[PDB]
Amino acid sequence: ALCKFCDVRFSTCDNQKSCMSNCSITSICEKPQEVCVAVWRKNDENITLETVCHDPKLPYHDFILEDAASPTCIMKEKKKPGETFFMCSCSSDECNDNIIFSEEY
Ligand SMILES: O=S(=O)([O-])CCC[n+]1ccccc1CCO
Image (cartoon, rainbow, N blue to C red; front, side):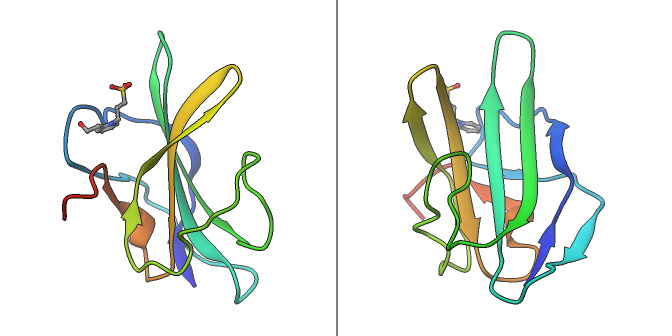
């Protein structure tokens, strides 16, 4: 359990099949059950990328990390009232550093 852990940073990730995190912090997750998470958001002022460790038995941003067992971080759209974002989780080393915006691969 070893993840990029910069929390929410500005990003230029847009209109590409995959993105790097460009996060310089790689952390040992505090608890062994934790997985890596990436969250991509765009509003009319900026794009951000959030990278953390998170326990997948706990919701994150009001969603369950159903993909926690995956070695790769495959972005999927999350829609709630007021906000749409993209999120993925994964459980291989620094896997939230290689963020894939496709299911084609
Ligand atoms: O802002 S949007 O509504 O179009 C969602 C964009 C989703 N997204 C984010 C970042 C990189 C790539 C993609 C899609 C693949 O090109």
